[PDB]
Length: 46
Length: 46
Ligand SMILES: CCCCCCCCCCC
Ligand SMILES: CCCCCCCCCCC
Ligand code: NA
Ligand code: NA
Ligand code: NA
Ligand code: NA
Image (cartoon, rainbow over all chains, first blue to last red):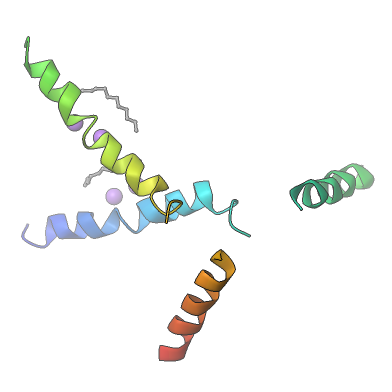
C-alpha cells in the first residue's frame, strides 16, 4: 500500500486531468464566424 | 455532531475549493507564443 495508494494518486491525476481537459479544451483554439459556418454546415445537410 | 458535520462542512470547502482551483488555475497567469514555446520544447527533447 506504500505504492498502491500512489497508484490511485497517479490513476486519478491522469484520468481527472483528462476529464478536466475535456471540460475546458473547447476554450483554447472570430467565434461568431466559427459558429455561423457550422450552423450553416449542419442545417445544409438536412 | 454539533461540530462533526461542521468538520465535514469544513473538510469539504477546503478540499472542494482546492479541487476547483485545480480546474480553473490554468486560466489566470500571448498564449499562442506561450504554447508554441512549449510545443517546441517537448518535441525538441524527443
Ligand atoms: C482513490 C481516491 C482518490 C481521491 C479521489 C478524489 C477525486 C475527486 C474527483 C471529483 C471529480
Ligand atoms: C459531507 C458531504 C457534504 C456535501 C458534499 C457535496 C459536495 C459535492 C462535490 C461535487 C464536486
Ligand atoms: Na481512479
Ligand atoms: Na476520475
Ligand atoms: Na470530505
Ligand atoms: Na471533495
